[PDB]
Image (cartoon, rainbow, N blue to C red):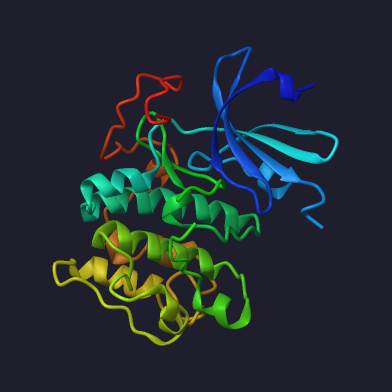
Length: 270
């Protein structure tokens, strides 16, 4: 049985309002993980069985006296946000790559009736090979939150929000900025609900089409909002050059290589 004594503490990753996430190293294998620690009283499974190439795998689950613990695989490449910062913007192809691996992960979750709710830049990390890895920690606080219109209006967390999350993630990936950066976050609520989102002229016709689809205010009209879920997204023009069987297989070549020697290389951890 796993316990607190099988790990060496290294650093905090995301903080408590619901618990903590800390970077640790399993003493026996020397491998690294992110330990989620949930306050049992501050809280006054699906996730654990959902395995997928671009989804962070749960390694261990144990309980302490008044704490819930989830030891999870920690990607070695840095957090996408870090990489996006350096490049400022990704090539539509670089974005298409990542956007493709997310769509794959989302089609899988939706197939299992699971709505992810947290598709967003900060939840994206790159693994040792440069393949995307979606996480459930909480890096960065004051980063403008971009909840789906149907969330802000009806607190509806249908599967459509994941496509919206994808849209906001793709937009910032190809536009180098959030849809409404030019405006203070105070009016962000009315904006998301009633403001048409503008796109850079440099944006390819296909890419403008994707985003406008992923970012429609009406869930039912949104790209991926129709009954065939991910099909609509997978078969959109922007993804013509995509071999879906190739992506889930990790046959595709990462547009960028992290620079880590192996999942033990404490580089990106800092």
